[PDB]
Each structure stands twice: as C-alpha cells, then as structure tokens.
Image 1 (cartoon, rainbow, N blue to C red):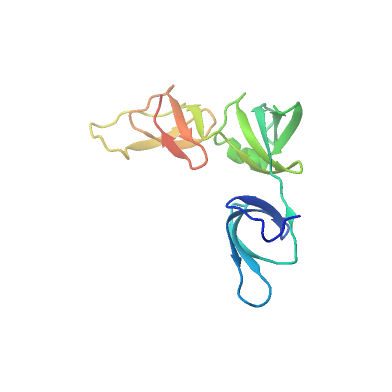
Image 2 (tube, rainbow, N blue to C red):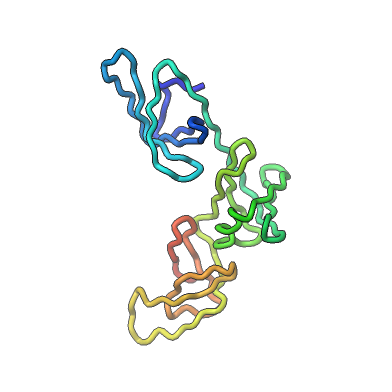
Length: 185
C-alpha cells in the first residue's frame, strides 16, 4: 500500500470507493503532531477535480490503470465488439460508451480502452480521427469568414459544423477528446 510520503504529479490511488489521479500533492505539517497530505487529485472515472487529505499512519490502496488497445469490431448497437490486441481478449462495450464512440470511430481502428480490474472505466478514441463527410452543402458565399460553417454529417452519423467550402466525400480530421475541427485532408 501507499504511504503518505509517496505521491507524484501523477499517481493513481484507489480511495473513497473511486480511482484517483494525483495532479499535485502537498505534504503539509500543520504542527498538530501528525502530518497530512493535501492532494489535488482527479477522479479518473468521472474526470472530476477534487482534493483529499491523507493522514500519516493510515496507508491507502494503489490503483493500477490498465490500458488496452483494441481493434474496432462491430455488432448490434447495444454492445460493440473490441478485440484486445494485447492478446485475443474480446471485450464488448455497452450502449452508454457506444454513444460517445459512435460520435467518433473507424471500423478496424485501434482505440485505447481504459480498464480497472477488467471493469471499463473509460474509452479513449485516437486524438485525430478521420471521418468522411457525407451529406453537406457547400456554397461559401464569397466571404472568407472562419466561422462560416454549416451542419454537416460524417460517416459515423455525427453532426458537426464544417466550413461552407467542404464538399461531400472529403475526409475530415477531428481532434477527438475536445471535438475540435481539423481541416479536411
């Protein structure tokens, strides 16, 4: 287990029935006779920013985060099949996760599924995904406004705002994670 003198700018600890990621720890000695550690740590499951004060003399359980890059297979949209490329472990993701993965994904593409003890805690899509734009209307009206965008549809079925000079068939690069539009190839 982890002692209160062992923390880093990134360290995963399982406490409060959650898995946390210490962003910045403060080993504080208030002069009470016991030292504490005010740790700024992010709930790795929800993405929430919290802080926890650890107490000297009470060790905590460490959390090892398991990253699995899986090839994107397909099934009915309640569960999608992902092939563990680490070694042949078929893992199916549930509708809730599929909702986000259905926003950005490519079939046959490797995504990084983040598990803890086999339990899916998150799914990481590649930071730059390439999606073909299907059904969009060009016609940039002479102006060169950078915010001249229209509601376009990509192959995934996701609707995103493309510049008015984007034509059907163009492969749009998107920064998955933030949703920032990158320019068509």
